[PDB]
Image (tube, rainbow, N blue to C red; front, side, top):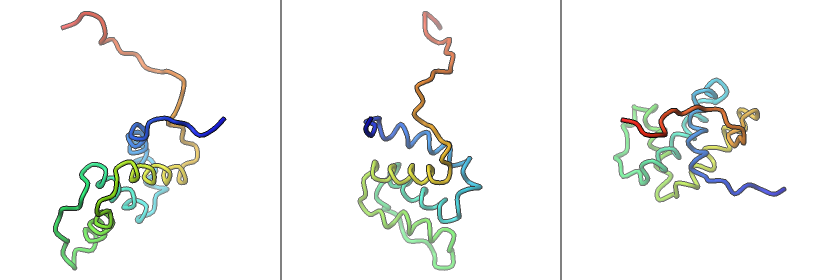
Length: 109
């Protein structure tokens, strides 16, 4: 009926795996957009020295991740996910079905 109240992180985990599959649909900038936030949720405050001027490739990275001074992790996962949804509308992370077998359960060693 209404929006879902499922966990946030859980998604950030799945989406991440999709990224590698949405690389062809993700533009150069799109790749970073996820990196920066992905770094703010894993590490947090840049707390890192600015890259060299000549080193552009690395520059952008530090920048995008730098802009996230003291940004929250969840707030970074929200945008990090949605995006992937725009690139691939045929993505269903929240699936009720159950397909998986795990022997590791009863007495073992």
